[PDB]
Image: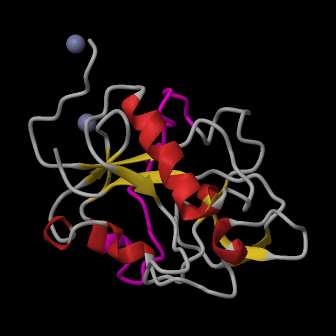
Amino acid sequence: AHTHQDFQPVLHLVALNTPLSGGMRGIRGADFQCFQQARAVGLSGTFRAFLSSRLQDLYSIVRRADRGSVPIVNLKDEVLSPSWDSLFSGSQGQLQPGARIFSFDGRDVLRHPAWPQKSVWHGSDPSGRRLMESYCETWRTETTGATGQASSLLSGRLLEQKAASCHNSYIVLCIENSFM
Ligand SMILES: [Zn+2]
Ligand SMILES: [Zn+2]
């Protein structure tokens, strides 16, 4: 009714309610939006942006203990991946077949027109390591001349390796750092 509750260990992967360009005021600005939006919908967990930053590899964002066996689920608790570790194995973040990703407000980012381009910013290599030459100057710039690594959500993969212009407005995801 007013709080989302889970009775099994799971980590939520949820999308911000609006696409963002590479200029997010740094990782702190992206993390903050993740926190606000999670709280505004009753999620009790600690949400951080699914991105690599100047001083942070995407892989290490989730607590080590929860990396090997806690399923990654969407807003509606549907399983996207059996573990955090599975995404960064070299599979390029292959999601489960037919998997869906909802924004905190409950919209299906892939089917809803509010997200014009079906790509996700990540700025990481396939192992979740920061790409210092491709992460929009640590998410501080939306200039056409700079790039950040992105992935086409239509491929069913979160970690494809495409260097996109920072001016683009792509989907930004938020991952819970530890369960319940
Ligand atoms: Zn309630
Ligand atoms: Zn849940």
Magenta-drawn stretch contains 90: yes
Residue 97 picture location, percent across and down: 42, 53
Magenta span: chief secondary structure: loop
- In this view, the residue farthest toward the left is 7
Q: Quadrant of residue 96?
A: bottom left
Looking at the image, is 167 positioned above or below residue 18? below
**Quadrant assignment, res 85:** bottom left
- Image quadrant of ligand 2? top left
**Image quarter in which the C terminus is found:** top left
| Residue 83 drawn at (x, y percent) | 25, 64
- For the N terminus, which image quadrant? top left
Write the start and end of the magenta stretch as one range. 86-108
Q: How far from the left and from the top, in percent, is residue 69?
A: 15, 65
**Left/right of residue 145 with respect to residue 97 in the rendered view:** right
Residue 148 is situated, as x and y percent measured from the top left of the image, at 70, 74
Q: Nearer the viewer, residue 51 or 23?
A: 23
Q: Is residue 31 left or right of residue 145?
A: left
Residue 166, placed above or below residue 180? below
